[PDB]
Image: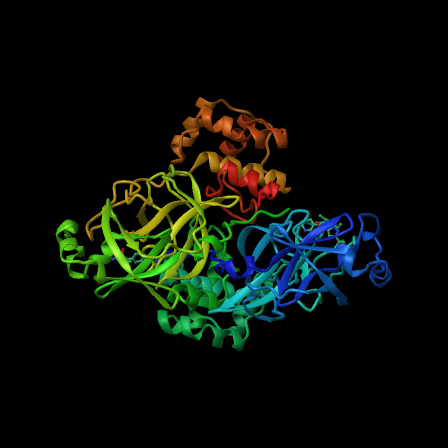
Length: 304
Length: 304
Ligand SMILES: *CCC(=O)N(c1cc(C(C)(C)C)[nH]n1)[C@@H](C(=O)Nc1c(C)cccc1CC)c1cccnc1
Ligand SMILES: *CCC(=O)N(c1cc(C(C)(C)C)[nH]n1)[C@@H](C(=O)Nc1c(C)cccc1CC)c1cccnc1
């Protein structure tokens, strides 16, 4: 028992982290096969971050201007191209540590692990969720760009995120591995405000199920509700509307605990209206929303 | 910016996880050089867990009874010995992935990362702290025994914990890599109750510093206090007494923020007496105590 904010083992991703330097800018790159992926803003100086014309800036760069270093050894750049907001640097050597991988574009509410890196070296791993406003609440400092978000299914790494920037409000924005930003963010130092950071309702319910499975049952009540009645309460509290798809996704947790999804919804409804009253659930004093129903099943079953 | 419960990259430890089977019991082992470390209770059947005589149980086991499997290949056991509550299985092959390592016995309040494993395969990584009552609040299921806790200093892994058991209250107990349990726990299925789980005061102050460094300053007040006055409040709230050693350890954070340690102590004192009033600090509704002052400095500086 015990429920923790658990990240995937980072080994397979550590073997892919490289350092990319273009001029005076140094950030992280992801080396898969003979291609190194990195944010295109590596070609930017501090000056042109305000209004960069990436295509124009790119014309002044040749293969030899991108310095790729894996560990203490240098990789030879034999080609370069810009795909949306990422640069793909073809190197002459396939990464011997390339795991089985896929590039996936995740939906908001989905969780992933981040391997925070600086100068191609990994410093930490934590679990995140793509917020409904397409930002991530990460822990990234200058030089962390190019650090990646991923999920692992047995031996296949699904890369879903690459860090590009910190918005003026301290939240983070990035792209999928095809270079498309999540949300409406752009790789420019401009006024970019995030939308409402709503709570991921399906994840809160999943975490309430995890709490029941681990012994924290005080919040269980004698009530039930309907999807529409629940959603009126969720709207008031800036919670994402709960759909029948979410109810279906919660099915296995509902089955294991014997607590119908709508009954857990009424427990959640009372927690929203009454608060925790100084109590805790799974060691937290607020309703945790960065565990999907799949994470609860996986953690509670011990999927390796 | 952004502050996350961050674990060390788990790569170096993943390369050391092996499966150990003795009879019908299967748990995790740690393979360093030509020795595999694992909980001695691997020799136990479900029956003898109530009152095991490990020395006697061990006499019935030979080298060939311990099956060690690293990945899909079997390791040859050429020797076995019991050191306190761990078994050391000498194998004929040195682990080619053995990183630079040390075995350390940590003090309560110290934090570490855990690589949760099942059948020698890693499933997740999370950050923990050794509680002042010598338990850890982990996330471990049956088969997780032998999973390890560690810290990394650049390229040297300091192993500090090995999981052995879950107490009837859902908390976890284990040993250092010399087999000595943290706390008064024994590897027996008997009534073992944990002591008071006091809050790690120095870690809460470190986390308040991290909050100030990241922009959360609402809890800062116009007051100061003394170590003795603070400690009277800390005693009331089951917080660990704060010493001049802790004040010294908080020095770098105090210097970076310009907030004297005793002033942060008065902020903490008011947070204890008044509560959060429905507010949050670094996304948490309670005072976080599983970041040491060293973790705050490291995370905030980007040590790789
Ligand atoms: C890896 C580069 C870097 O550290 N940052 C960065 C990104 C950019 C763009 C994408 C605009 C070219 N410029 N610099 C920062 C960052 O995003 N800095 C920043 C902040 C903190 C607030 C508002 C605007 C900007 C853009 C300059 C960075 C710092 C911490 C975490 N991630 C990225
Ligand atoms: C790896 C073996 C295992 O899963 N567990 C275990 C440990 C033991 C001892 C050390 C007593 C021989 N026996 N079984 C359990 C565990 O500790 N089980 C348990 C629980 C859950 C509560 C009270 C007593 C016991 C001891 C039998 C385990 C389960 C989850 C996490 N860690 C360990």
